[PDB]
Every structure is written in C-alpha cells, then in structure tokens.
Length: 46
Length: 8
Ligand SMILES: [Zn+2]
Image (cartoon, rainbow over all chains, first blue to last red; front, side, top):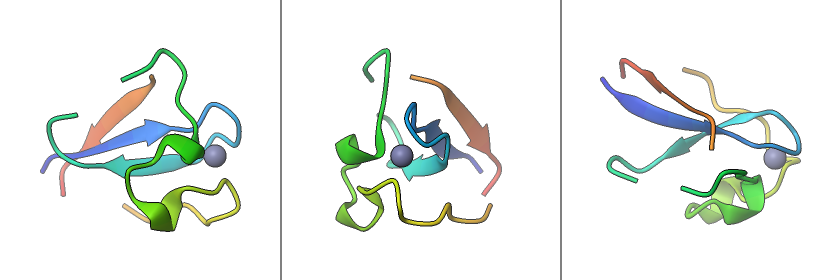
C-alpha cells in the first residue's frame, strides 16, 4: 500500500488521509478533503 | 489520533 486511515472520534468512521500526515482527537470536520468533512458521509471501502 | 494503514 499503504493507505493511511484515521478514525473520527465522534462517528467512528474511518477516513482516508494523504500520505505523510495529527491531534490526539480527530474528527471528520478536520478532514483536508472537503468531500469527507461531515460525519454523515458514508465510510469509503478499503 | 487513531490511525491504521491498509495495503492499497
Ligand atoms: Zn465523523
């Protein structure tokens, strides 16, 4: 791979991050990708 | 943050 994923501490979904990227707690709202910046967006498959 | 790597 290797694709980095981070887990949102509010909704528990896993979100892809860019290679080479963090706060103790992370939330969808902090996503650099605006497409996955809301907890309502479904989790991407592996 | 909690992170994991998958083999893309
Ligand atoms: Zn979330």
